[PDB]
Length: 429
Length: 80
Length: 67
Image (cartoon, rainbow over all chains, first blue to last red; front, side, top):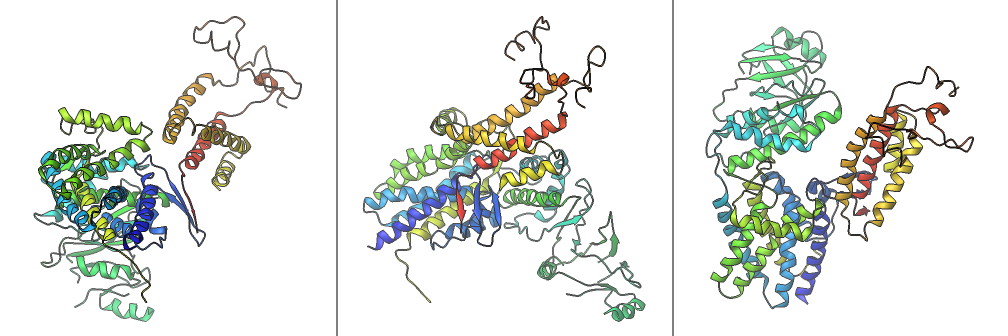
């Protein structure tokens, strides 16, 4: 029974998707996970659940790699991509009973994913990066899910002005790993310095003889180290020394990387800033500095501003924005249901099941919010017929970038494909 | 283990009323489990508590009063 | 307390009084203000608000994973 071995992995995969399904949205149900080491952690983020779950099932681990690529590419939708993956697996259960080979099932997802993108771009409003008024309100709504609210008004232009300098045109993939969030003890949220040149993680020499400041530094004025007598020797030569460089920042500094080098300490920081690198090969790497008193401030702020950069990253790679809340998923299921008659053969029936699999995302959002499951879904197909993208989330300031909805369908087509293509597994060592 | 951190939170600040907090949180869980047979969604139960919590503070603030009955009656006498 | 809130919004009262307490020492119902039992407002507000904070996190757990 080669197919029955794969069906056992599909049922185990749907059980994982149903567990993450309850955690979708801010009102979703949390999951308690007790690690073998004794650490007790809980949260509604689907990326952290699957990371510490330690899944021993070979096929179920594919959701972890997709969730890792979901946060690395789009940055949002790690929970919704698991639900969409399990929806295609549930619809494929009835397909195997009809004698349909998974190759046609997997090949039809490629044509269905590419068609869903073209349909989504027709209803999407194309936006440009030259308008700074749209990017401020876009990143400000992502900060409403955190304790910081009134202080988030000054954080919106911080993330917008950093991307626009490195955006240029036709940049395609923009790596956010080059943007480092500096977490230091002391200060406040309203106090921030861009320092577009670069920002280090370490202080300077507190001993005697250290210049701590140099003008026109690279005849080596400033050096880095991954003895007390060596500091006194280079002090006469007017050479600044910075030691105790973290090993994690070695690869970081080799990418982004001086007219003026000085050490400016707001309170207690004792940090050195560099401006005007003016390198031809190297671009303008900006590291964001975050100041705060309590440890819970700079922590929750780090994850809030990181998601705001991912939303802006989606707009740079793919222009346009749509309204969140499962609004576009309803119209896509309506158009693909009528266009299913244009096909012929076994592939025509797949378009009908593919439209029903896209309605699980808006249904889960209505279930986790306390609203009636089937009643709200019926109201979506009714209102979206006359109006277009009018349901109102635009007044509620809910904006989901188009690249998240595009990558969620694209990664789900490859994830479900890699599942059904496994007909057996054996011990290999 | 959640009630363990809840008991220590009241001791490090108010230091009084820790026993009453555990009893209130215990009855809320018993009545919430009975709503499962009624097909009541847990988020609505959570939303119903958050809306009622903010409105209950406003009702309590209406009956609050400072020290009174100093003339003609006695208040601080019966405390000691 | 039922008849105490009936005439309360009308801003007129005759036999209706508020702040009925429970005295377990003498086994009778008297006002706690005159009985000598008084508590601050800060203690009651933070105790009721924190009681619901721990109750929400319990109802949100639909799954227990223990290795």
